[PDB]
Image: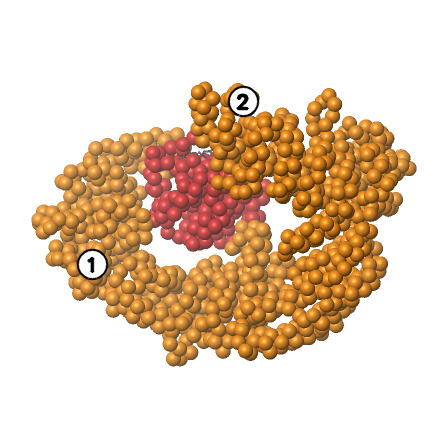
Amino acid sequence: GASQIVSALDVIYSPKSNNSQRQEAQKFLDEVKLCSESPFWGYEIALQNPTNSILKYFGLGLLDHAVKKNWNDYDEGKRVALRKWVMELNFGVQDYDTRYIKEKLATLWVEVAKRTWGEALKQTNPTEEQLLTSWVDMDNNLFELWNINQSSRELALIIFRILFEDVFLLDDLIVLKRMTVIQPLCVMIVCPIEVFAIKYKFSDKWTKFKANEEGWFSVWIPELNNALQQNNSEYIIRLLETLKTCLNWPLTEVIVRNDVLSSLLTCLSSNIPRAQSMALDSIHILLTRPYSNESHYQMTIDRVFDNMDLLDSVYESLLFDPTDDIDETKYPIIKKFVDMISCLYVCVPKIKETNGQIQKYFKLVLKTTYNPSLIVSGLTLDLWCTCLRNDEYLPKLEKYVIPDLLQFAADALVYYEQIDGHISKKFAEIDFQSKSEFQTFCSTYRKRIRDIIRLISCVELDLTYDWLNNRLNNYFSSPFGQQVLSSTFLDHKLEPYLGALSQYMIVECFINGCIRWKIWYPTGDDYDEKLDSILQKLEILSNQLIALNLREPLLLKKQIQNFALFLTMLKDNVLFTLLEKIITSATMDYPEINLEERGAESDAVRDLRYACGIELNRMALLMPESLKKIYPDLESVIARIMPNLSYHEKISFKSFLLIIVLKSSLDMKEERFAAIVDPELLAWSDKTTVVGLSDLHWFMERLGIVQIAEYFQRRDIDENSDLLSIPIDDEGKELKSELTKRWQSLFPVRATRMFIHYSMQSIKTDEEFKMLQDLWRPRIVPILPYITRLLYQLQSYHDPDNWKGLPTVVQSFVKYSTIERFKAMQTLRDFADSVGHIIRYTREYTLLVLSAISSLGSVFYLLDESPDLLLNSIAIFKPGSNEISPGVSTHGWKHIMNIAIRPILKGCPKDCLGKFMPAFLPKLFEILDLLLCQKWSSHTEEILEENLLRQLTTVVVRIVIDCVGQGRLNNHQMEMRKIIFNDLNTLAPFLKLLNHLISFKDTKCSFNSILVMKCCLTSVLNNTVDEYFTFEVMKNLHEALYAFTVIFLTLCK
Amino acid sequence: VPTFKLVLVGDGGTGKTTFVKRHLTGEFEKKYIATIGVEVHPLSFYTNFGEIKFDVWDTAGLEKFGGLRDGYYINAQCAIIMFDVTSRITYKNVPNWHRDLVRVCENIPIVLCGNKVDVKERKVKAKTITFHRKKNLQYYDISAKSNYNFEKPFLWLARKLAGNPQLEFVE
Ligand SMILES: Nc1nc2c(ncn2[C@@H]2O[C@H](COP(=O)(O)OP(=O)(O)OP(=O)(O)O)[C@@H](O)[C@H]2O)c(=O)[nH]1
Ligand SMILES: [Mg+2]
């Protein structure tokens, strides 16, 4: 009895029922759904229980299950009966049927249609019965449904919506099997028969499936127009919902004949927000759809562009005040609208501007660009960039919009995420999940704004130059400008600094635009004097900026970085007048602050000087020849600046001089090179250091741990006390500074690295390379043993067994100094962390020095002691316990292998490769094998340690693949493979290392090692190697299985 | 006090029943148990504007077991479309769930939730979640195993239903 079904449904939908009795009722209803005659019960329920919506929906659900899961099982009679039932239920729709009931009825109708409609057309002259089974009346039935009552009209609209969605917009499996007969039928029903005949030549068997001769579009559009005039909001929304699905695919002739776009524009000007959203989606679809005939496309775009006043009015209507609370009913519509507008610019070249259509369009786009939201503006920034970079548009923009777009882009280049209460934040809480996304988007937005300004400067250089001069003059007269000029340090989180920085980024964009102009201009005869004018204007601008005597270090850094761009272009004579100002302004002293106390001000000054050095060196590399003209004046200037410049920067400027001396074709290179370099490398050969390096205790003393012990004694520090609770004092700060200053110059690793790196940074000819090798060999070869000794000491430092000889007072301090983890110090714990930082920094620079020495080629590799010196320093063995370099961080090994060993291997010359690799690789592979075996033996902070171990393993894998490649090769790998495989002494530890890699827990490392083996098996077997391989590889072990099988089959042969 | 029927829907095995459990009790379930039919769980939240109740319908996400697959959405007043970033299939079915959902209830607020964000091996990425940007759905990365965004969906739905963006939860 149906009453059981009603009771079960009440149990399920009753809030008070517990989930167990819900399960009971649900099991009963599933059995009912699975019963025979289920569709008939569903039809009976739906027809007899019109008042109870839940029960009727359940009956329709039974019918839907029938048609959607049992259509194949039913014979013809059942299928036709199902169709009759669905049609009868649809025709019986009434005003009391809820919306979801109408949706379900439409779904049933569409399902039956998809599975039966027009299947007979695949045959020639189908019989009348074949027409009946194929549902020849469907169009006629729908036309009947359309006229029954208003509810049936809405139902027909839903049927069309679902039908077209499934047939065209979605990947419906049932349609994929019938596209060739469904889609033409849809096109037939919507389009008039005459229009249809043009594209399709099919015979009379088709036309019998059409009842409305003119097609449905002749019905929907008059209905939509008549609803709009009557302001029937609901009916308009439904009609647009149906229409939005059937504008893409149908023949264009019907769209033009009915003047659909006129109706869509009328909807868009209607105050109904749903109608506006649907109409915008529809217009975008209508613009982007594929057009077979271009006359219709021309008519469409002309219609859109002739109604730019209407679109402007619509946009004005959508706008709202976001200060209090953004309106979420209209904000999505604004985003959609502005998205549509941004896609029209591709149509501009095809528009015949009879009444200023293009002007109005571009002004509208600009108006939408001023939108408070950053997403809305970001929609149009790409349009602006693309329009600026295509020479077709530039006449139009120039006459219309460029002078205003420039002003916008200039005013929109601010830091939104840091301004308090900025109007853009209101929308950020809606459009973005978290402040991270908002900041990333703001960065992208400002990038695109800078591109806009750069291109506007490139295209409209004179206009932008006048505008820029006016802007800067007006700014540095404003009170904020005066504060910036009349102050030495600014809170770089507050209005004055941010405003000044925006001005300097605008200046940078102008300079980048001026640079691009050199490439963009068509190099006519007029080019020379134009470029001369640009250079003069840049010179005047630079002199204007210098005259401000800006001192704020962090803004002065940007000013220096901007001036660096000028000199890419400026003439040789003015080059000095600018470089002298750069050097003498970046390296000014700041009495207001005591440097090296690590305060924000000191850090800002240090960054300023470091950036100045970097820019000078970069420039010297880029144009060494130009600087030759003025080189002595630069020598004089830098000598003038040296006294107040710290060592860490004395080096950075001496390297600049060195670059000029070497790569500028300046005469008498050797003596200048000596004068620049020898005073700096001298510290290596100091006899107290040469002797000192051979003792670890002396190394600790120089590091200052003895002085740390004295300091702890004078403060009565208990070695067991928690250092984190003890604060630093004046003596502590002074000792820290003294130690770091003495250490830095005791081991001039940075000076060596800089000089070698920049010396070899670029070479034109092998003759120049030989000249550099001759210059460096006398100075490096005597020093390499000491660099390796330094690295040796830094390695043995981390071993707890070594500092056991130091005073007990400092044991905890040293132990903390070796901590690995990833601001001014305040506690002895921070002091120990800083000492650890000193040690680690020296280690990194020693590795970089060793890597750089490798670039000298024959000078380093061809030596006999290079491999032993390099290996003995890194791998510190201990008698008894055979662990290598005890106590050194896994991150430490990662850095060692990544910076020193891998580049040294990669950088081996092939004429020297004969001597080096046979002596280097054996011990290298042995060390790697022992290392990774020891670390993996031990296998949140623990997860981070495991990740570091996996990183180290990947680095070793990278080294191995560099050595012998993976399963094509290049000259390096081919050459090395000869050494690896010919030398059994190399091969044995190599195979051990490979096997250990294969069996390690990391998936990527093991898989890549397996590929290496797959690429290596055929060569190694080609005696002792054979047996060792067989035994160990087999007992150790998806191409891994393939390699295992190959090994078995080969060795067992 | 007001009671809002919420229907929780999403591809099977995406963590729908774990999420409502976590809100019921602070625990967490390791097992994947296929929910059969629907589980009805009355949730409640306390806010600066009193108390609200979500009568959450936790629907089954598997074709085999969905009893009244879409009959549960009847009279719904909000919904959450749940998918897990760990498998792209569950996200690819989001539009299908949205069709099934809006088809029965038109204008209800709907929240799109990416579950299992705690695991670093997310296969769905920000460049693919633009489905919500397209359907005007509110999106949240969440995890039943981590509370960092475990309350955002219900907060947003409470704001939408109560018509009061200033509503906020307290405990
Ligand atoms: N990684 C991760 N896994 C989760 C999280 N939440 C739930 N899970 C997993 O999801 C499974 C729980 O299964 P269910 O919650 O029943 O899956 P469902 O989405 O409810 O799908 P149905 O059971 O078919 O209704 C457990 O195995 C959990 O490990 C999460 O936040 N992060
Ligand atoms: Mg579940």
Residue A676 % position (x, y): 79, 55
> Are marks 2 and 1 in one subunit?
yes
Read off the residue under disc 2. Answer: A1023
Q: Nearer the viewer, mark 2 or mark 1?
A: 2
* Amino acid beneath label 1: Met
Question: Which residue is drawn at the image coordinates 43% and 68% (left, top)?
Answer: A345
What SS does tag 1 mark? helix
Question: Which residue is drawn at the image coordinates 82% and 46% (left, top)?
Answer: A683
Is the distance from the Cβ of mark 1 to the nearest ligand 1 atom less than 8 Å? no
Labels 2 and 1 touching (C-beta < 8 A): no
Q: Colour of chain B?
A: red
Could you say which disc has been placed on residue A188 in the image?
A: 1
Residue A444 % position (x, y): 56, 58
Residue A906 % position (x, y): 61, 42
Q: Residues within 10 Å of mark 2 (few under 14, many from 20)?
A: few
Residue A867 visible in rendering: yes
* Chain designation of label 1: A
Q: The chain drawn orange is chain what? A: A
Front residue of A606/A749: it is: A749
Q: Is residue A481 above or below residue A121?
A: below
Q: Is residue A612 above or below residue A32?
A: below
What SS does tag 2 mark? loop
* Chain designation of label 2: A
